[PDB]
Length: 110
Image (cartoon, rainbow, N blue to C red; front, side, top):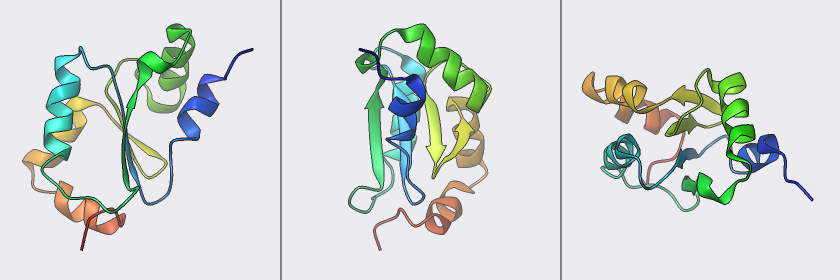
């Protein structure tokens, strides 16, 4: 009668994929999505996951804390590895490292 938060998350991750967990009412979420949307992704290599799908919310927050070190969306994954949140993405974007990293992990179209 209850999907574990761990399964909800891990089912959406893959080695050569970007996965971002969001709530659409969060401004930091839309800011993060705006960074990622600058790029063109291969089929299936990018998923935007709406966490309002999961209940209870505290269980998913608690899981994100254990594997990412923070509770609140956005939570960004490059492959199965957590990058953290909006600030972490911005940092990599501002230093012009995001393109190289997305090339390495095989998610970019062409």
